[PDB]
Length: 146
Length: 365
Length: 97
Image 1 (spheres, rainbow over the protein chains, first blue to last red):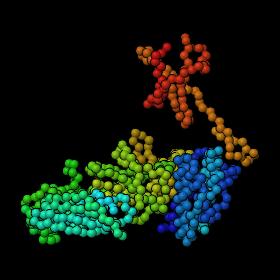
Image 2 (spheres, each protein chain N blue to C red):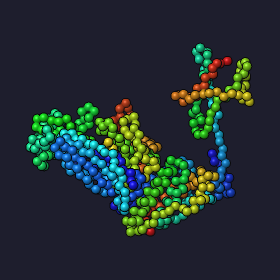
Image 3 (cartoon, rainbow over the protein chains, first blue to last red):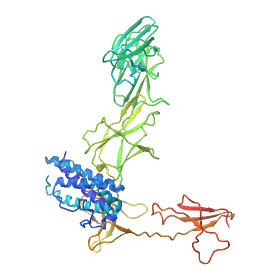
Image 4 (cartoon, chains in turn red, orange, yellow):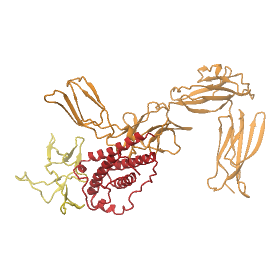
């Protein structure tokens, strides 16, 4: 397993998800950094310093995206899974043992927001995902640690 | 008291042995021991033999041509003071002259296959030196191929097999075993099918699904063949050497107007190695085409670059070309630019850009 | 369009729904060359944007002539229209007055 190739592919998957969100016109007009109350469970821009943090963040995003009926969103969830797997192989090449992140146990609340306001959940989840991926991409050269 | 064994069948093995087979009754949750009675009635010898077996099959060595085999089996519980079942209904199997072992061979291109035969002439087993082999009754097989395995039985060995060409309905080549000039009606069936089926996949421009295609053109020769794509998903990446995995799942493929089958994988795992092959489930046997592993992220067909702008720079006089890098793939890209005078036929000049962070190029015109 | 009510900078999840649909639908009719039936057509092109919308042509027949100003009448009947290959709905009035 080439380490350099895996690192570049990890970069690529992150850029890939970011660009996908860029294609989604309604998400572009929405501020990534902006805080919206109720959506706090979604892992938005809050410093993601380490690989385990990245893994749990991506896991929660996958869990949220899986529940929303949209063709683009299902794939984004899949991309997030592959990104997690890439992080796991990098952690292996670095001699780190990454436990497989479960999603949020606290999904019993997400149903309410999905029912009441689908639009808010989708736009927030996508814009915060794009932001989180951008800082992850920035930090992946900084020699990320476990 | 178990019920008598059901479904008593008799097939000839590739070795030329008579394989008696049966099914266990479906209602016994415990192993059975079987007793097989068989008689061999030839024109010159009657042999009776009782064999006890724990398997659901029996081999009988060296089948005699022009003999009649009657077989009965009964079952008893293997463990403890079991009662014997009643006997199965008697099944008579009267053999015909001339033996092929095997009766049929289903193989792929480039393999080696060999047949053995025995020729019975007027209740006598002829010497192997007399036996001659023929293909499709058209022509005699070269003597170099023959090998005398034993005094009674002759063998032909084939090397570097080529695809069987179909003659009318028949997909296979009829191999005949003859006593000198004179041949017999029965022949052996050799089936060679090109398993070299190209499976190509393409992920849609939004990377939401992956469509895989393969052509039927090599397989339209076999009526009764059914085709099923199988796939095995790896957790990450493709192996250096793809191989058939015992645990596989089928995929629904739909025949398109262009004659190709189209199978859509949705959702798709971009970084999971999808090993695929075609399962050809002939009436006797299953063949898997050579497996190929495909990574959906590495087989992306990108969307064309959008927002393409071509302007010639004022004062400088360079054809400045600009665009927006296409959404997919986000990997570093090399770009190819064709340009030419606009007309009924455009004489395209080609230019390649290998800078990943490049969004505009200026080319003299 | 989702309209939101927010306390200063910070907003809430719930919004108000505003639906504006182009109702400017051209209905054109044509009586066959034998004047035995009248076929009316209208395009879907403005309304293909709303899934879950159902479309029903309604008509009110006057005893004689058309009014100077057409208006919706409370007593109306529906007409069976059939979508054609050209993307237009076709409704045949037979017999015709």
